Amino acid sequence: KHTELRAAVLDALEKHDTGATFFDGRPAVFDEADFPAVAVYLTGAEYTGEELDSDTWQAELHIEVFLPAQVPDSELDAWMESRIYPVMSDIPALSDLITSMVASGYDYRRDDDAGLWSSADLTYVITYE
């Protein structure tokens, strides 16, 4: 498994997140965004993802924060930056590979059950360039 990533991200999660509700991966339940929760998912489990025994760290860190529909964009956005950035920066591997974590696209979603709720999908690709 690519579980080395899981360990790194979980450690950072433990140290820097709000600590409200965490998901190892996005659950197969009804829209999470009914309640405030955060899930962290890194690429390599969806597919074989080619297991790497390499010294270099590369992964997509896809972090999803789920918040009530009554939560405005600025608050969702704030939640994302204020927690997620200190979390990712806390990952030692990111410090090893790159000077600072390089941004990738932000997408706003809600797409499991009905989707009228609020979730913020932030994607970070590491070793992107």
Image (spheres, rainbow, N blue to C red):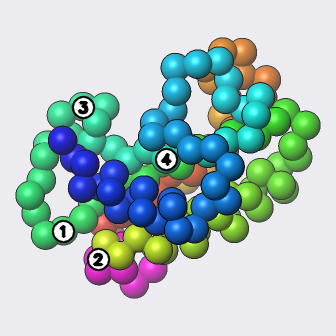
Q: Are marks 2 and 1 in contact (CB under 8 Å)?
A: yes
Q: Which of marks 4 and 1 is nearer the N terminus?
A: 4
Q: Does residue 96 belong to the magenta stretch?
A: yes
Q: Is residue 46 above or below residue 5?
A: above
Residue at 41% x, 58% y is 9
Type of the residue with mark 4: Val
Label 2: how many Cα within 10 Å (few below 14, some 14–19, many 20+): some
Residue 96's image quarter? Answer: bottom left
Q: Earlier in the sequence, mark 4 or mark 3?
A: 4
Q: Residue 56 placed where, x, y %?
A: 18, 68
Q: Quadrant of the C terminus?
A: bottom left
Task: Please name which of the two marks, 4 or 1, marks the residue nearer to the observer.
Answer: 4
Q: Are marks 4 and 1 in contact (CB under 8 Å)?
A: no
Question: What residue sits right under mark 2 in the picture?
Answer: 97
Classify mark 3: helix, strand or loop: loop
Label 3: how many Cα within 10 Å (few below 14, some 14–19, many 20+): few
Type of the residue with mark 2: Leu
Q: Residue 119 placed where, x, y %?
A: 69, 38
Q: Can residue 59 be seen in this view?
A: no
